Length: 193
Length: 56
RNA sequence: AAGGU
Ligand SMILES: [Zn+2]
Ligand SMILES: [Zn+2]
Image (tube, rainbow over all chains, first blue to last red; front, side):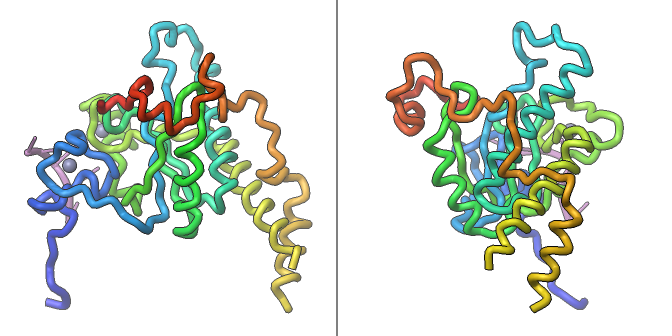
């Protein structure tokens, strides 16, 4: 009785797409019956189909478990370092799904909204791994409401075709070295004044 | 001002950390274009339809 | 046109 109840962005909302409002990508895409509101101002950007997991390649089950971990760390390092040039990066999420709307999706949330707009203006004219980079603003705010809950513990029975984010987490050593390196880069660009 | 003091206390704290702008990326795949596309920009390649997304 | 409130 303290506040009115709403259904906006929920699965019960029959005009707004709940999956696009939370996860930033719907299985129907532009043919969906519900609205996909593309934000003009946002902190999170989306690079669809950027991470090509070698496991889903013809010659990509020849690598061992240790080699696969170092290859993903080289990708996560290559992403966080390049995205850091557009401002402060708060979180970097890489999707390990197989659905055409979430396969290899890369979400990056900046601290400032202007940092995200300057990123999509530059990424849409660059390349990565012999492929043009697609960049757009994503309405994703909280990744906890978009990640698969049954995937954090054990594995999701739906497999790679899950409509929620199956985020592939990097090594804790790299994630810690990236946060410490970003604060050092920001602290160095502060003693100038 | 204490702002300058709060920076020097962090820089001396982060003495054995390399800043992100000086990370030596050994195998970075950025700006690598496919053979023949040296004169084709990223915008012209997406509109050509040779590099479509898995949705389309 | 669903599993997510
Ligand atoms: Zn939708
Ligand atoms: Zn799942």
